[PDB]
Amino acid sequence: VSQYCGQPGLGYFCLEAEKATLYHRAQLAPTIYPSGPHMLSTAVRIHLDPHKNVKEFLVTLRLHKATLRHYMALPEQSWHSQLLEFLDVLDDPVLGYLPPTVITILHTHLFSCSVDYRPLYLPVRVLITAETFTLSSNIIMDTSTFLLRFILDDSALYLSDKCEVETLDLRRDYVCVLDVDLLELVIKTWKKLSQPLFELRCSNNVVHVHSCADSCALLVNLLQYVSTRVVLREVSLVWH
Image (cartoon, rainbow, N blue to C red; front, top):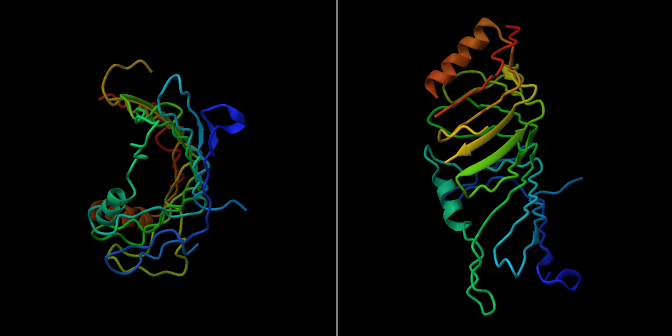
């Protein structure tokens, strides 16, 4: 749209689809999403001001039940391909638009974007079932400071059979290992008035942990084989 209700700067840019999450390229597809909002509902909002002459974005992104991973090889190789193809910020050399300085303010909602096929040298069918990944960065990301309220809701984790890549079991949504009730990691990275660079004040709420000797032993094998940081974070209400 252009000039919504007659006033320049007001518009409605949108996008909708329903897709299978992750298919790789050159070869063979990753084939992710083996799992009534739609996918990639990037209903961004723009209220820029001609007098200000600066690029404003209100991106209300919504990847519903997707799996937005593109890191095919051990390094982020197909992710590199994705970030070399997709990354281009509205090249506008046309007349009447001298390129306004780019500034981004995201309010993304990666609701139910399950991540269970993150590839590495030798993971074991790793399953991390996030519910809500609310990267509501109310502050400007492209700056020294970035307030990012990761208000998650009741995540969890489940581990597969055996560290060597091939792993089968009766339930691939296996036993719980390390679930979180909530983790409000409200980071203010300065790249709480803490002058020190990268103050990752992960003010985590709590970390429940349940386990059996085999379960935690296997988890430790998994971790083995696979600048203020003031948490004030409860370490474990471990029922283990």
